[PDB]
Each structure stands twice: as structure tokens, then as C-alpha cells.
Image (cartoon, coloured by chain):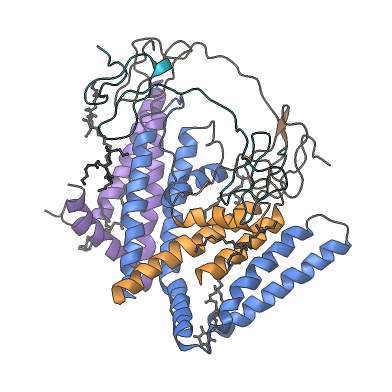
Chain colours: A blue, B brown, C purple, D orange, E cyan
């Protein structure tokens, strides 16, 4: 329970080291996949620079606020968001079995794009159940984008 | 080198000739051959019929954007 | 009074059941439209998982806040 | 803090994919900056070698910057 | 009818044929004629010279995206 609640930075530095060592092992085993390990070290190694924001008061307090935003607000948001995303993803894949929507993975990505403001409400394709598709997408967009995503900003303000 | 049909792609290895094969988006995709363009035939809705609600239209028509769209000739 | 002011979850589970039954009726009548009734009952179903957020304090209070946000703020903005 | 995150994920993406709009730190930094202002280019029409590792990095970057830090900035301005 | 060259466009009146027409974006636009096209003449930068900072490459070359770019023979 102590690791599960405290000493996060030690875990992050350790995980960076593990990715490095796995990369070396894959290097000398004559594999090409070692690059896939290596970048996961590198992208972590820069973010751990925030460890050194302590020792400067303003940035240190800023980093602590980031920590509490991640644990208290974002963790509750992502559970409900994933439930809504998976529900509407399964419905859309069931409805339209062909073309960008023939798998859960592709449909999950295409629905995820709407939340970050680069959706694709085009409806140029010749689907069997167009005009039901539109109702499902409008319902999804209203529920996620307008309601939940602004509610996150309100809760972060209170926190 | 390239990955042939039936082999795992995109984890550091592309598929072979891309006029014949492709790597889908499925998180462990396998190279697959393309499939031909079968034309639309019966089971489609005809001109002046309710398109969109569970029945697409054949080649020579367009299904508009409307609540109850009817296929029509597009000029 | 309590059919709309209160007891939302009973209504939503009931409406899911109605969509399922309409799907069965359309299925045996030889109509492809039974797909359309099916998926709504699916899409509602995964939403009704939020009913079970009670029994956990933080998620329960979060879900109550979502209810109030829908009924107070969004219903004027949409008008 | 934003520039620290931007430079980190930019270096990782450039190292992973050496060609095709991600052959430099300048180009990759600009392409990742475009995500911050809501006009990204998540098409994935290209046939890269390490796709499906590329996607994980982009999703991680988007969640860290767009959802968390910007809304945090709005919260802190509201406090100020 | 359509508007001829020099007349005011877009206030309820399009101009005539597209081969000699473009209604600019100017809030009281006038119908204008397409000018002919000339390739990049002299005063361009040459391959291996700096581009972007007040000088543009000639048509056979291209200027990459960088802080201090140089004209290159693309492809
Ligand atoms: C692909 C890769 C991307 C992933 C990047 C993920 C973000 C990294 C952000 C950089 C984090 C570095 C850091 O600065 O570490 C952070 C931990 O990361 C997190 O916030 C959540 C990680 C989830 C602070 O950890 P800290 O050691 O200060 O813990 C405190 C104790 O010290 C103290 O005694 C108290 O007990 C206090 O209650 C404790 O909390
Ligand atoms: C494809 C289309 C999908 C549409 C989905 C629309 C969002 C559903 C969101 C998830 C709903 C599940 C749920 O859990 O429903 C919520 C409320 O529903 C809504 O958010 C708005 C529905 C309109 C709780 O319902 P509850 O039975 O607890 O009612 C409370 C009583 O228990 C208690 O005694 C008190 O008197 C309290 O004042 C009562 O309210
Ligand atoms: C934080 C933001 C999240 C947005 C992106 C969400 C993507 C989740 C994909 C869900 C899924 O359901 O993904 C399927 C299961 O695999 C996994 O992906 C496991 C890892 C998933 C861990 C939850 C994909 O497998 P498949 O073979 O392509 O199924 C297609 C069948 N023909
Ligand atoms: C929440 C976000 C909302 C965004 C989407 C809004 C779309 C509403 C369209 C309004 C409309 O007014 O829709 C017209 C009237 O019919 C109906 O649709 C009734 C059912 C609609 C129930 C309200 C469309 O009819 P039409 O035949 O196609 O008109 C074309 C004439 N040649
Ligand atoms: C709220 C969001 C605002 C975004 C749009 C801003 C448009 C204003 C353009 C300013 C301008 O500079 O507009 C000039 C005059 O036009 C006007 O605009 C008059 C009204 C100005 C009163 C406000 C340009 O002159 P012009 O004749 O139209 O073009 C020839 C030029 N060679
Ligand atoms: C505030 C929002 C910022 C978004 C845009 C940030 C773009 C900056 C890129 C950083 C970089 O790292 O830029 C590299 C170093 O040069 C400089 O640019 C110095 C000036 C930089 C001052 C720090 C690019 O140089 P290059 O020659 O093209 O390297 C490619 C070798 N083939």
C-alpha cells in the first residue's frame, strides 16, 4: 500500500531504467524491436525533469498541483469517459460493419478524435443505416463533448 | 525486408507491394490482400424509395441528407 | 409525479427492455429494421453501468453531480 | 512545463520515424504544437514501420497536454 | 444575368464565365481576369543556398522546413 500511494518518483525512475535494460537485451538478441523499447525510455526521461522543480518554490507548488490534478480529478473522469466511449463504439460497430468501422480499435479511435476537436461529421459514405448513425453520433457528441468535458474544467476549478 | 500476407505488420516491419496488400488498423494487424469492387445489385433501394433506413441505393442514384431521404437522379 | 420527478433509473432500465422487445418483434416479422432497435438497447445498456456507482462514495457523488448538471444547466443551454 | 513535454515527445517521435514529415526536430515540434490549438492531423494514412507504437505516443501526448495542462491553466487563471 | 469584368460582384450577382473570372475576397469585390502564369524567373536562390529569409528557390528545387533551410533538388 505504501508504493501504491507514496514514492511515485522512485517508481518512475525505476521504470525508465527497466525500459533501457530491456532495450539492451533486445539489441544484442538481433531484433529490430529494441527501438520500440528505447523511445519509451527517452520520452519518460524528459518528463522526469519535473522532479527537479522542487528547490524552486513556485514551480514546486505548481508540480504538486499537477500531481493532485492527475490523481483526484483525471482518474474519476477517465473511468466514466471510457464507459461511454466503449458503449457507443460497440453500437456503431454493430450498426456499420464496413469501412473505418469494421473493428473496435478503429471505431474507438475515430470516436476519440471528436473529443479533441478534429472529428469527421461528413456522412458522405453510402451506408445501410445512415440517419440512425447521425442520431447516435449526435447523442455521443452531446454527452461527451459538451457535458463531461466542461464539467471537468468546473471540477478542476473547485479543486 | 517486407512482410508477406499472413504475417504481423507495423511492429517495425511494413507489408510488401502496396498495390496488392495492405496493413489494417487492428493493434496487431496482419498483411491482407486487397479485395475487388463488387458492384451493387438487388437488395438496394430504387429511385423514389426511402433510402438510409436500412437499405442503400444502386449505382445510378444518390441518397440525400434529410430525415427521410429518397434516392434521386443527380445531375 | 414520481414518474418524471424521481426514479429515473427504473425508467431507463424499463426503456432498455422495451427496445429489446421491439427488436424481437421486428426480427420475427422479416424486417431489417430490427437492427436499429437493437443497437439503442445496447447503447443504453453500457450507460446504465453508472447505476452501480453507488456503493462507492467518490464515484457515487460524482454521478449525482452529473445528474444535477444535466437537469439544471444543460437543459437551459440547449433551449 | 509545456516546452519540456513538447521537446520530450518530439525527440521520441523523430527517433522512432526518421522520414516523412518527422525527419527533423523543427518539423516534428510544429506538428505536435498543432495538437495544442486543436487542428491536429491524426489521419494515419501513411505506411510507417513502427505504427501502433507511434499511436501510443500520440495518445499519451494528447492526454497529457490537451486534457490535463490546458484545463489546469484555465483553472489557475480562474483562481488568480 | 451575369456581371462583366469591372462590375461589382457577390452582392446578389455572379460574374460571367470562369475562364476569365475570379471574384476576390474584398467586401466590395470586382470581377477580375486571371493573369497568365510565368515560372520562377531569375533572382531565385540556387541549390545549396539559403532560402526563406528574403529569397525563394527556383521551380526545379524546393525549400525544406527548418530554421535556416537550403534549396534542395527534391526527389
Ligand atoms: C510514456 C510515459 C508518459 C507518462 C508520464 C507520466 C507523468 C510524469 C510526470 C513527471 C512525474 C515526476 C515526479 O515528479 O514524480 C511525481 C509522481 O508522478 C505522479 O505525480 C503520478 C504518476 C502517474 C511526484 O512524486 P513524489 O515522489 O513527489 O510523491 C510524493 C512524495 O514524495 C511525498 O513525500 C508525499 O508523500 C506525497 O504525497 C507523494 O505524492
Ligand atoms: C442512447 C441514449 C442514451 C441516453 C442516456 C442519458 C444519460 C443517462 C445517464 C446515466 C443514468 C443512470 C442513473 O443512474 O440515473 C440517474 C439519474 O438519471 C439521469 O442522470 C438523468 C436521466 C435523464 C439516477 O437515477 P435515480 O434512480 O437514482 O434517481 C434519484 C433517486 O434514486 C433518488 O431517490 C433521489 O430522489 C434523486 O433525486 C433521484 O434523481
Ligand atoms: C486513454 C484513451 C483511450 C482511447 C483509445 C482506446 C483504444 C482501446 C481499444 C479497445 C479494444 O477493444 O481493443 C481491442 C483489444 O485489444 C486492445 O486494444 C487491448 C488494449 C486496450 C486496453 C483497454 C483491439 O483488438 P482487435 O484485434 O483489433 O479487435 C478487433 C476485432 N475485430
Ligand atoms: C441537438 C443538436 C441538433 C442538431 C441537429 C438538428 C437537426 C434538426 C433538423 C430540423 C428540421 O427542421 O428538420 C426538418 C423537419 O423534419 C424533421 O426533421 C422532423 C424530425 C426532427 C425532430 C426535431 C427536416 O425535414 P426535411 O424533409 O428533410 O426538410 C427538407 C425540405 N426540403
Ligand atoms: C469580429 C470578427 C472580425 C473579423 C473580420 C474583420 C473584417 C475587418 C477588415 C478590416 C479592413 O481592413 O477592411 C477594409 C475595409 O473594409 C471593412 O472592413 C469595412 C468595415 C470595417 C469596420 C469594422 C479593407 O478594405 P477593402 O476595400 O474591403 O479591401 C481592399 C484592401 N486593399
Ligand atoms: C512557443 C511554441 C513553440 C513551438 C515551436 C518550437 C520550434 C522550435 C524547435 C526547437 C529546435 O530544436 O530547433 C532546432 C534548433 O534550431 C533552432 O530552432 C534554434 C532556435 C530555437 C530556440 C530554442 C532546429 O534546427 P534544425 O537545423 O532545423 O535541426 C534539424 C536537424 N536536421
Foreground residue, D18 or A21?
D18
Nearer to us in this view, A81 or A17 = A17
Counting labels gives 0
Q: List the single residue furthest toward the left.
A: C1
User: Foreground residue, E60 or A30?
Assistant: E60
Quadrant of the rendered image containing residue D5: bottom right
Say if B31 sits above or below A147 in the image: above
Image-quadrant location for residue D59: bottom right
From this viewpoint, is residue C55 visible? no
Q: Is residue A86 above or below residue B43?
A: below
Q: Relative to residue A144, is residue A16 drawn left or right?
A: right
Q: Is residue E58 above or below residue A108?
A: above
Q: Residue at x 21, y 48 (%)?
A: C78
Q: Can residue D9 be seen from the camera position used here?
A: yes
Counting from the top left corner in percent of width and height, residue B31 is at 73, 37
Q: Position of residue B45 (x, y in %)?
A: 41, 14
From the viewer's perspective, is A58 left or right of A106? Answer: left
Query: Which residue lies at the image location 72% right of the left edge and 69% below the top edge?
Result: A19
Q: Is residue A71 above or below residue E72?
A: below
Q: Position of residue C66 (x, y in %)?
A: 29, 61
In which quadrant of this rendering is ligand 2 seen?
Answer: bottom left
Would you say C79 lies left or right of D59 here?
A: left
Residue C36 is situated, as x and y percent measured from the top left of the image, at 38, 32
Amino acid at each position: 500500500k505504501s508504493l501504491f500511494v507514496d514514492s511515485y518518483s522512485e517508481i518512475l525512475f525505476f521504470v525508465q531504467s527497466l525500459f533501457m535494460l530491456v532495450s539492451v537485451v533486445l539489441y544484442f538478441s538481433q531484433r529490430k524491436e529494441y527501438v520500440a523499447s528505447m523511445v519509451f525510455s527517452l520520452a519518460m526521461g524528459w518528463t522526469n525533469m519535473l522532479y527537479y522543480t522542487r528547490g524552486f518554490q513556485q514551480m514546486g507548488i505548481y508540480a504538486v498541483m499537477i500531481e493532485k490534478m492527475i490523481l483526484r480529478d483525471l482518474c474519476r473522469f477517465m473511468f466514466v469517459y471510457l464507459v461511454f466511449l466503449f458503449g457507443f463504439s460497440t453500437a456503431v460497430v454493430t450498426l456499420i460493419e464496413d469501412g473505418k468501422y469494421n473493428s473496435l480499435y478503429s471505431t474507438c479511435l475515430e470516436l476519440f478524435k471528436f473529443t479533441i476537436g478534429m472529428g469527421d461529421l461528413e456522412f458522405t459514405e453510402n451506408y445501410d443505416f445512415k440517419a440512425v448513425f447521425i442520431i447516435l453520433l449526435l447523442a455521443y457528441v452531446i454527452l461527451t463533448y459538451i457535458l463531461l468535458l466542461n464539467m471537468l474544467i468546473a471540477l478542476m476549478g473547485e479543486t | 525486408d517486407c512482410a508477406k500476407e499472413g504475417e504481423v505488420c507495423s511492429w517495425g516491419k511494413k507489408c510488401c507491394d502496396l498495390d496488392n496488400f495492405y496493413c489494417p488498423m487492428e493493434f496487431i494487424p496482419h498483411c491482407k490482400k486487397y479485395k475487388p469492387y463488387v458492384p451493387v445489385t438487388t437488395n438496394c433501394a430504387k429511385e423514389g424509395e426511402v433510402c438510409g433506413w436500412g437499405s442503400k441505393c444502386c449505382h445510378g442514384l444518390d441518397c440525400p441528407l434529410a430525415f427521410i431521404p429518397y434516392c434521386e437522379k443527380y445531375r
